[PDB]
Length: 57
Length: 111
Length: 37
RNA sequence: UCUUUCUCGAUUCCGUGGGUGGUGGUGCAUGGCCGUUGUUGGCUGGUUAAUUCCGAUGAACG
Ligand SMILES: [Zn+2]
Image 1 (cartoon, protein in one colour):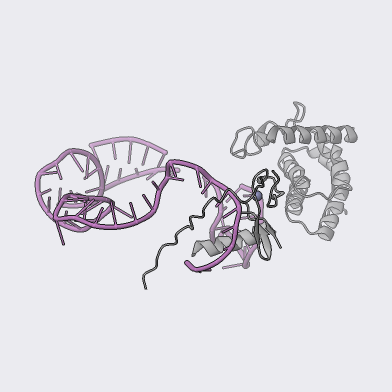
Image 2 (tube, each protein chain N blue to C red):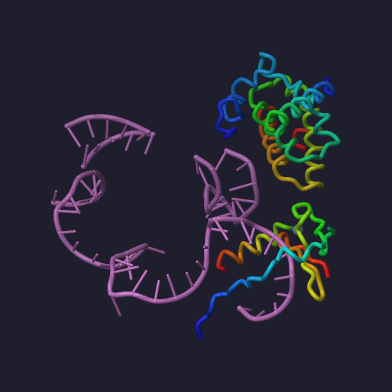
């Protein structure tokens, strides 16, 4: 019943999904503190901003 | 912080402010503030002038009190009627106090 | 004279003002929550 | 905590030692400090039956 510590998934080339070749493949969060690079997590029903907890659905 | 100061109403108002203009005392301040006690029902500013006139009134302007007792009395009846219609505490308390001072110093007197 | 005295009193009040110078309920609730959390 | 990728970036994280160990427990010497083996003075606020309640707020002598 020992509780194993959570391990972060070491994903290969996390940078190489928001750009082409130019434009932003993901959305940009329109808040004041976040923008110009804060890409927007696109889950199968929603979008989330990972810094200031913006929520769109 | 400001009540305990010597310049405040704790000590110096009881001593040097009673000498209105160098001579104690003049009710020209009291008769001049009628425009504040009339048509203004703002709290916490009526209470301050009521407290000030309560402290100042004790320094025996007795012939002036006998003369304009009618003016003071009609002012006080409108004050108590307005305050009883309104329902405040502080202003009523020190206008009762200055009633006490005025009636102690001095048909309408029964009223 | 009474009007002039009232104007002087208003000026004194302004001078004193110069010289001296829904979230509450929910944050009191989270205060009571975190007091014995 | 189990999925789905968004962000923070060296503020790091994996394994093996019969090697110490430290937010440890415990005794001794150890420096400071209490208590221990007289006499005379000295009110903005709401609240109650009420100088009611809470609330701000000194001296010498042997
Ligand atoms: Zn953002």
